[PDB]
Amino acid sequence: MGPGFDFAQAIMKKNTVIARTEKGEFTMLGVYDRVAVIPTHASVGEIIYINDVETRVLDACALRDLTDTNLEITIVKLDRNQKFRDIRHFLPRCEDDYNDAVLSVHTSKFPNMYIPVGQVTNYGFLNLGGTPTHRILMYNFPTRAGQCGGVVTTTGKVIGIHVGGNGAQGFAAMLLHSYFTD
Image (cartoon, rainbow, N blue to C red; front, side, top):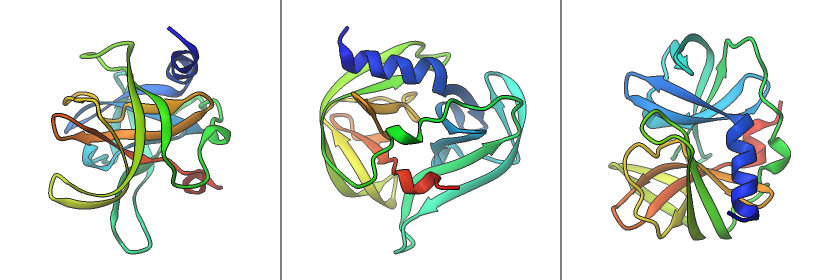
């Protein structure tokens, strides 16, 4: 509908796959080469389905901060025959607050879904499903189940992936450029 939705669509159309684990179907962001991200509660194993194709997992790393606190991001390297467009230059370098974000989801349950969530707060600490979690972004949109792995964007920045909600607010794990140096 406007330039935020433009940037969100450009990311969804080239840098997402549908990931399936034993814990469900998730929006999965591809970042560069065969490297993607997914919420850690997806419980990635040795095999994952990518657009309904059986795919070996070459590596999976559940990120934690240097206090050994959960960040809810798992970085997955896929045994796929095709690379993602490199979008690392759209990742923020530091923790921040944002205006006018979009949450974008693509699954069997919610295809081509885009949500203007408005202002995004650097919330910080969240007890997420009983697990102390850091680097959480918050938006005042009543997000539901099925949206996990959804991509949070502003114009020109890919800032997080949706990991939870409390019925009135939604929560995303930050994406930082420093997670994807090689």
